[PDB]
Image (cartoon, rainbow over all chains, first blue to last red; front, side, top):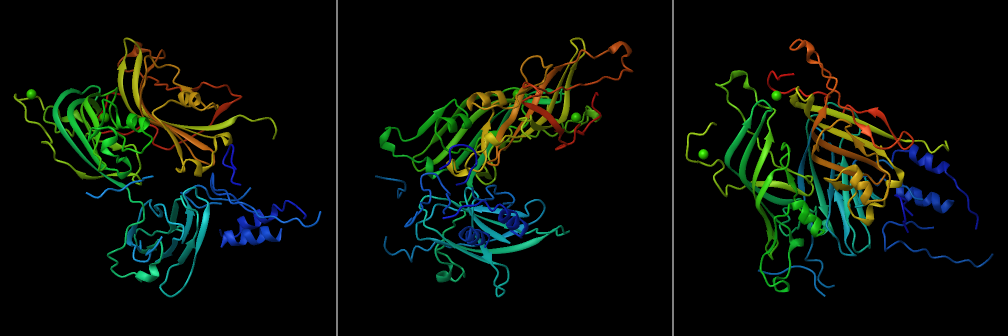
Length: 73
Length: 286
Length: 161
Ligand SMILES: [Ca+2]
Ligand SMILES: [Ca+2]
């Protein structure tokens, strides 16, 4: 869900280094981001049809070139 | 006439929507962007001839896989999102170069270009969401004034825009009258009234507010709307050069710009609905 | 930085003509183009909610847009105009990243007290077009001048000035 701004919606961490590493590469990109996120969940792309998540607990934002002029993540 | 619109899943192979075109690259338009219409849940977009495919919001959706046979890059994507819009963007300038000319052709299909296998493809339907086609006609009745110290000229004339917008269509019975007319309100004001896109225009040089008379924008149920306005407008004329007065020849340039980009509306055809310059009694100054 | 620094608004101005100079009243009517450009993250939005990428408010002043959407904007003024200027093609459009820009082709009659015609016709005059911001330096400041277009236009003819 999105309220204000251009925000695009076990063990948890915040590996922001992968962001810079991907930005360093020549931006397939979605597939690599999905693989990195799986190694480290779902994303939203529209209002009213946000992608749902399936979870199973048996034991106890994203990156986009939202501008259409020049493709820059 | 056969009616189309909105009211209150078989044999999809024959209704293949696949069409192609050739493009020219030069000057600033090195980067090219194209849209597409809403698609069925099962439709898969195949792009053939870098290039990338995103949605209307710019969120990346697919890239192109480079297959050496056939040159260029081959791109393919599929989704089941129902009401959504997709965009394909191609960049031809990955590095600084002299360039100056580029010829390029593309292959585009919304379900299956493989079935059509390119070719002439007569039954293909264009899916680029092409810009609406608005014809424009202008006539000059008088040049009422020329203020040559301020370098402006006040001119009276008639203007007539005419464009086909199927989304603007309606059922004639709901209001009784066949033609739905919005009187004495500018195209921008009408677009404010009804939340729809319209080809708002401007004179690009007028100083002060022009006098709009008899202006009316009326729509036909088929969707072919037309706007008419008898204006008395004071244009600015920088091109005036009175260094050779009185033996000078001047250019009265009346420029009707569209307040919407070429993606939305473009002036297709000039309409000679009336004599471009009117003949009136008297010698007249100009 | 946690000082809530003032937003950076770049400004560009070009003069197409000096249409009039009323030297008894000491004013000059000038036509030109003005372009403000500022980044406001609070002004960002999701592109999908409205379809179009850029959200544009047409033929309405920056102050009028700030009235429409309850957000701060760098409203400006000419500080010397007498009467109402003719604003043409004025549009303020916002990019989802948040970088908004305002464009306006004005025909405005500025007042020029600095006129001193004691040496007419051998006089040199200063046409000073001063775009003030209607918000304090805490909120917005003119950071960089933008040379988007030739500052003074070259037009056919000798021209008076
Ligand atoms: Ca001139
Ligand atoms: Ca006459």
